[PDB]
Figure 1: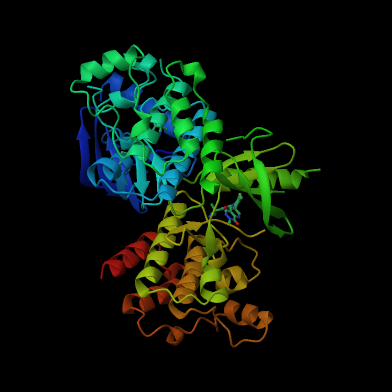
Figure 2 (figure 1 turned 90 degrees about the horizontal axis):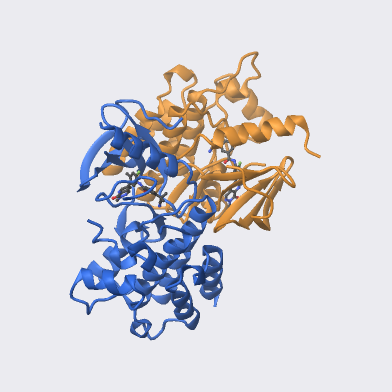
Length: 258
Length: 250
Ligand SMILES: Cc1cc(F)c(NC(=O)c2cccc(C(C)(C)C#N)c2)cc1-c1cnc2c(=O)n(C)ncc2c1
Ligand SMILES: Cc1cc(F)c(NC(=O)c2cccc(C(C)(C)C#N)c2)cc1-c1cnc2c(=O)n(C)ncc2c1
């Protein structure tokens, strides 16, 4: 039983607010993050999200701690101190060492490898959803508040660059692998893909039809050969030609030691 | 949480005791695997340990990840890189800054406070069982495979169960004494049976004059309340945690 009774969680500072939820910093036997989401759609979506998080016990996956029903639906997770991968590469524009870049990728592949072993498809893997908690441990969660956390979907502008061709035209282990390849492109170039394109509808049409893919010539000079090859396999147009996370993780782990 | 046979790559042996061997390993990253024909007593003890760990989802508590039955009973937790609090204070005589000492105590009280909210009595809280994982996050587990941390009632062989929230609080007070003095209690006593006889009869308790000069007044008072002979006079972990949290901000 993970239900936290009414009056234990001290809800504090509002961290973020979206169209389908408000996240708050809080106290409950230490620091926590509380997601406040009642209609039957919200009730099914709350229980689906608690059911998926309930299945995760991994260091590289955001620690679910509990949930509440009264006086409002709430999901309690650990507090993540620091910034997302998107904030480090694109806002702080920090230049991590190659060792630190390969370690973030290794930690992300461990979390994704664990998720796919537990039959969990992320569906929204992106640098925004990869937290560099305490600047050392990588925490994969779903910190987005603009979409509903349901089994399947029927305003996705902050996720288009990580969508595979079949996801634009769907959700599988291979579509997460594509998104991870995009994350690898961000680590290896320091930039988001398709920066020269001026419209979102041009990326949607060109990526979807297979005539558009990240430019691997824009990668850092010190980027390893195995990393260039790994990104290329994860970003393949045909999803069946994409590697699985065990093979991705073992390539990053063999690269990290070399 | 059952992990099928052939997923965990069991590697380096980390420790071996009378009833368990811990190994470093791989399973979607780094793991610690505790290995135990299996006896019905040991089958009950394995399921009891998996049942308690199953109830814990806290940053300051060792992350249980899974368990296996074949080809032998195994409990899979996260890997803890670094050293225990006992190793930092007594083996390597690391002299942490007072801010770092209060932070370890704060993290330990958060984990213990969480455990007592989930109706879980540790029963073996000691510096050995407090891991300074990545030298920043405190992980409370049970890495044993303890007399100095036993409360007077626990030390006495009574007809009743002496283990309670208050006996964990006493053990925590001992842990506070170790953080504030850098030493284990009762170093002048020459025999274990003398500590067993004197602590039990209430005539023996740690010497709070041996604490560091820079030790805060609220910390001296907190240790004293946690180390009281009468267990009902000991504070609860919410009050302990709020006193350490108030002290940390000062
Ligand atoms: C409170 C909360 C409650 C939740 F329920 C989720 N939800 C998931 O993480 C989630 C949902 C669906 C599928 C998945 C899977 C398992 C596939 C993954 N990965 C994961 C996230 C948060 C959350 C939001 N924001 C923050 C934040 O801003 N900080 C700084 N720190 C922590 C923090 C935590
Ligand atoms: C593998 C393993 C399996 C287990 F089952 C337990 N058992 C508990 O943690 C346990 C049991 C009973 C009650 C409790 C409570 C909840 C009271 C607490 N706390 C906790 C511990 C470990 C373990 C051993 N050694 C190591 C180690 O050496 N390194 C370096 N890193 C990790 C590591 C992990």
